[PDB]
Each structure stands twice: as structure tokens, then as C-alpha cells.
Length: 242
Length: 167
Ligand SMILES: C[S@@+](CC[C@H](N)C(=O)[O-])C[C@H]1O[C@@H](n2cnc3c(N)ncnc32)[C@H](O)[C@@H]1O
Ligand SMILES: [Zn+2]
Ligand SMILES: [Zn+2]
Ligand SMILES: [Zn+2]
Image 1 (cartoon, rainbow over the protein chains, first blue to last red):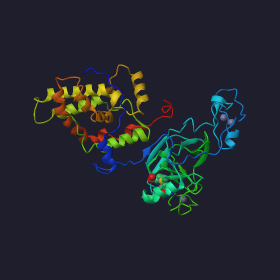
Image 2 (cartoon, chains in turn red, blue; image 1 turned 60 degrees about the horizontal axis):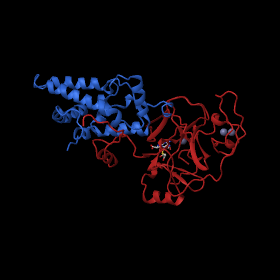
Image 3 (cartoon, rainbow over the protein chains, first blue to last red; image 1 turned 135 degrees about the vertical axis):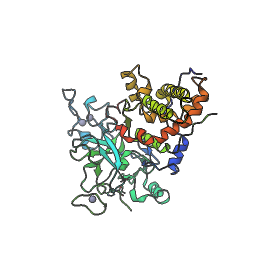
Image 4 (cartoon, rainbow over the protein chains, first blue to last red; image 1 turned 60 degrees about the vertical axis):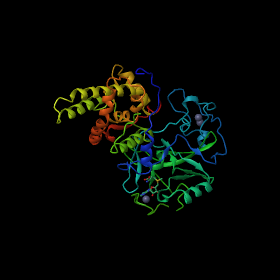
């Protein structure tokens, strides 16, 4: 043919370039960290069930269709659950469905940190309490993460993992999202909150304060139960992460 | 029976491009500050001033025409990531009578040379200049690799706006 109706094939780089990058056998290693990007958590052998579900929050849908509902006055927000879209009385004006609606802040820029390797910044200002991005990875058990840590993962110096309370770990060594590049600060500007979305536990990043564009996203590693093995710059710096 | 060899000096930029599009959710500044048309004209001008005076220029212009045609026929269907499809639809809507060689720039031109070998060896749009393009592409790629620094950069990429993810 010449003269042929092409069929949409999504672009993906060829096998050789991928194999050369993964094995550091090209003209120069690109400043690109090897991790697989996922859209949602991958339950390896455990599902992080929250233990409970949502309800109908009695929140009164505002007369003005643009005012947000369930804004810090909601029952589900008091139990860290996201409103079900077909039971929330606020309907389509519900603010308490940010995670399941995939309402990220799409102003995130990766960069090379000064003494931390990788880091993330925001190219737009962010009001306080705003939802940033979900921390994605492989939901593994305690034993499976110990397996991966002792016999598979070598770069323990920068652990790409977050912990869940029930002994489960969100391992972002192999698979995850950009949130694996968010480093630590003793005086953080963000916070990791655990929410019950459709009865499953999810972890989201939220703004602890107002911040202008260009600031680096940081959260406290001590306030989240994992560092079983620092140069942040704060005045009351804890010396080492712990 | 045709496979295009991408220079070793260009594969790291393809890795960077994949990382910027699929994993950092960035977009190339469309329309390009220097489009495929101007890049092809720069290559033509760089090929004119050499040893063989005037006895190679016809084939050079014909190869430029073939490259532009294959880019314009393969861009929207084979040279696009899944994340760039809303941008492609917006470009098609705003500029209907504008071939892709006027909109896109160096990275998509490079992406052409990783899948053109399928169409050259099985569905060639022109069998009268097929053998000439096969002769010249492994030198056009060398030109691109020599100018990689000025052609390919992360400065032409921007973080996608939040309304783009809603598409
Ligand atoms: C999940 S990684 C975050 C991204 C990481 N900085 C990178 O380059 O990929 C956490 C690691 O970052 C490093 N890190 C975090 N805060 C740091 C700081 N204030 N100074 C130096 N390194 C830091 C620590 O080594 C920690 O193990
Ligand atoms: Zn509510
Ligand atoms: Zn609600
Ligand atoms: Zn510190």
C-alpha cells in the first residue's frame, strides 16, 4: 500500500534502548531514575482494607452550585473516609472525594536535590490544606517487604517506601509514582494523610501551609512509622532523620 | 528487511523524552519554536555547502521531501505517546490546514526514525524515491546527532496544566 489507513499504536521506545538504559550500556546514563510508573497501588499479596466504609454525611448541598460541600464540616472527613458519590447528599459538589476523583495538583516538577539526590517542587502556588498527589507503590506485607529488603533491594540508603499501620508497607522501590522523590524536612510544609477510599487505605500528600510556586515539597519522615535502618536545613534540625 | 540504526549519541535523549512525557507528565511547547520544516531546511543548507557542488542537491531536496511526507503521515498515529493525544487533538482543531511538520519539532522528528522502517519495508508511500531515502536517512540521523545539543533540550518541555489531565 501507500495508501493505507494507519491504526493508532501508542509510542514506546524500542527494546534495545530500554535494555541499554536499564543496564547502563549507552553513550551516557540519562539523569532519569529507573522506576515503573503506575496509576494505582499494586496489591502484591495483601490488600490494605481500612476496616470500615463511608456513610451519608448529612452535609447540606449549598444553594450556589459552585460552593464546595463537605468542607471541614463532614462526618466522613471526621472518620477519614471519602464520600461515596451515590450516597453523598452534596452530590457533585462534594469536596471529600479528591482521591477517588484523581484530583491531583498538576504543577509538580522533578529536579535534582542539593544534597538529597531527587526532589519535587510546585510550579504554582498552593493554598493550605490543598490535596497534592497520592503516594503510589506496591502494597506488600511486613514479611514480603523484609524479603525484598534483605535479599533483593540494595539501595537501603534511600528507602523508597512508606508504611501502613497494619504492618503493611507501600514499597516504591520498583513500581510507584513521582511521590517517591519527596524528601524529608524537620520543619515540613506537607503532610501524609491516610484515608478510607471505598474501604481501602490510601495515602495522600496535603499542604500543611500556604506556599508559593517554586518551593520544594517536603514532609516529616519521623511522623510516619518507618525508618528502620540528614541535611534538611531547619533551625531545630534533628541532625539525622529519626 | 529494513531497520534504522539510531545513533548511540541520541538514545539517552529518547530516554529523557520518554521520562518527560510518560512519567513527569510534561508537554513539548506546541507549536515548536523551530518546527520540522525549519529543521529540514537547516539540514538542506548544511548539505549544500560541501565538496560536491550542485551534483547532490536534487537528491537532498527529494530526501527532505520524503522525510517531511513520512513525518506528516506517521505523526498522529505512530509517533505519539498516549499522554500527548489531547494535545494532538487540540493542535488538529486549532490548526486544521497545518501539516504536523509545521507544529512539532526535533523530538517527534527523532521519534519518526524508530518506526519508519516498518512503513519503508512494507507500505512505502512512494516507490520512486524509496531507495534514495534508505540511502540518506543514516546520514540525516548523523546530522541530528551532531546537532543534538541545540535541537533536543528539556527547555522546550513544560509541566502540563491541570485541565489537561481531565482529557
Ligand atoms: C524516598 S527517598 C526521597 C527522594 C530521594 N531524596 C531521592 O533522591 O530519590 C528518601 C531518601 O532521601 C534522602 N533524604 C531525605 N531528606 C534528606 C535531607 N534533608 N538531606 C539529605 N538527604 C535526604 C534520604 O537518604 C532518604 O533515604
Ligand atoms: Zn460531608
Ligand atoms: Zn460528601
Ligand atoms: Zn532536618
